[PDB]
Image (cartoon, coloured by chain):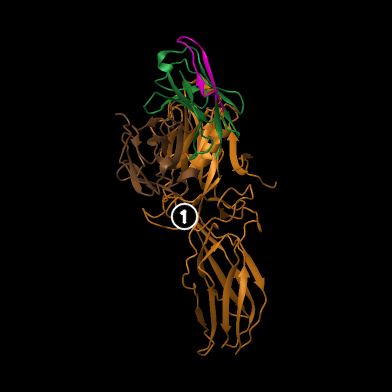
Chain colours: A green, B brown, C orange
Amino acid sequence: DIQMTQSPSSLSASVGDRVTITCRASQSVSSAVAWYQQKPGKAPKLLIYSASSLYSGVPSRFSGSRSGTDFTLTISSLQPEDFATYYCQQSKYDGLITFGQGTKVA
Amino acid sequence: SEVQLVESGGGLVQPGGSLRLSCAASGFNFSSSYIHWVRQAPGKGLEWVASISSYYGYTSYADSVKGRFTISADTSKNTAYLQMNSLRAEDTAVYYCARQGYYYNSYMQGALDYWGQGTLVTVSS
Amino acid sequence: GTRVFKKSSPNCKLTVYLGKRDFVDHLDKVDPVDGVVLVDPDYLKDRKVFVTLTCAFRYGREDLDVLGLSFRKDLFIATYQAFPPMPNPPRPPTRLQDRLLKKLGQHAHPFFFTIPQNLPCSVTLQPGPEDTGKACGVDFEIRAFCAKSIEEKSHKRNSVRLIIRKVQFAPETPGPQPSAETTRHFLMSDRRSLHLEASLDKELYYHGEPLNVNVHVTNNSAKTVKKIRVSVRQYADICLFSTAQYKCPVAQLEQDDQVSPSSTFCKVYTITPLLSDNREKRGLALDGQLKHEDTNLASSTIVKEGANKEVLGILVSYRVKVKLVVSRGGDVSVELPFVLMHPKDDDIVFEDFARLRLK
């Protein structure tokens, strides 16, 4: 399957800071990624899709951007809601899905 | 109305046994949307398992579960089953049921809009 | 890798992508329309990109005037809308539509259609020059246009219109040989007669598939046959607000055999009903406009049921007719009905929707 990599797998920023998380692709992915935010012991909620489009229930602070084969998430202002683990997902095909290792945003 | 995706049926089984994970769905027609089962080992990142589409009958599985898992969609009960066989220690993850989203403002491609509550499947002696 | 057909409206702000221009009917199911419509600016965002499919009977004119063309008779119409996308789609997008939405941005919206099998196969007819008739046919048209509502004033400049062909296919059923015998007695024969036999090898044939006709002849009268004849003349009828019974002999062959009195003769003859042999209007029926060569002879129409076919388009039927040119006194002939029908990862290549031709 497609190998999808996230880096770095551990971070720490204070409330009100700006944070960046990068997920890399080993193969050409046509902007078909989406990020999930998993609170501890809960179902991973959706954050953004299509690598740039926002989704309901998510403040406008999250904004991903596709800069080529790589992928990246931005958080304009960190809040207590953002303490979670973030998962980058590749969906180039229909029935095939792959996730990254995830990053623990303390 | 809201799509209350919910799953149940997982239990405890020694390795090499069998179990049938159930995913009850509501609020949407089963045919029009894919179903993906995504597992999560304790203290590890998520991992895809398998997928099925009722309308097309197009099944696919992850490499590690290529011949061990079986996913089947029963449209009559509006549910999709995952019948697992030859379980081993690594399959002790919690398993989710997920449904792809089709449109919010675009064509989110594999976004897994709605997730179930997750069922724990312990495999130990 | 795989081909994809696209056509752009003159106002390039809207475009349509399709997987195949021709759709096959299996007599019990029609493969769906699996297109996707793209609009880069959303066209001011206060409009909904409707994509309408219509199947309408035609008669009289293609000039857009009123004399006769008033018979534009939509036998089927659907109004799938794309943006907003409506609650849930009718079945998930096919893999082709997904790859199309991958190769394109977020500004592309799928659209899905299904055609009930009762509808007529796409066929059109052009009368001979100038055989007192008018152009007519049953065309399938996709009109993807952006508007605030369905009944808004649709216009060509901002609406893309493309034509689909609904060809028919049926299995090669091993039916009984379509025999056709006749016995001709003569006034002066004193109980003698000309015998004659014929039979096709198969009952159903595909486009371009040669037809084999058996022949058996035994002569008892004192009259010798000079030559024989074979033809596959087409029977086309305009059953809606017309009575034009076109009878063009689309394909014919001549072969000169002779059989004297008290002689018997059997043989097999090969014929090929083919459009490209005679690309002339000739007052015959086509499966598509004869301006382009991707068309063949109109597939024979199955009556099916559902109030027959009188208001459901024009019918075409084929049959091999053979006859004997006896010396002096007769032109004994035969008829052998049959039916004719259409025979039936990497990135994507954008083929154009232009129906290529030679002109």
Residue found at the very far front of the displayed protein: B125
Q: Quadrant of the N terminus of chain B?
A: top left
Tell me residue C216's x, y (percent). 57, 81
- Location of the C terminus of chain B by quadrant is top left
First to last magenta residue range: A7-23
Crowd around label 1: few <14 · some 14–19 · many ≥20 (10 Å): some
> What residue would you read off at disc 1?
C26
Whole-percent x, y for residue C59 in the image: 50, 45
Residue A17 is covered by the magenta coloring: yes
Q: Position of residue C198 (x, y in %)?
A: 54, 76
Q: Position of residue B25 (x, y in %)?
A: 32, 37
Residue at the spot x=52%, y=71% of the render? C335
Residue at mark 1: chain: C
Number of numbered discs visible in the structure rendering: 1
Q: Does residue C201 sit above or below C342 in this rendering? A: below
Callout 1: helix, strand or loop? Answer: loop
In this view, the residue in front, A31 or C242, is: A31
Asked if the stretch drawn in magenta spans residue C329, the answer is: no
Q: Judge whether residue C67 can be spotted in this image.
A: no
Res C272 seen here: yes
Answer with the quarter of the image where residue B13 lies. Answer: top left
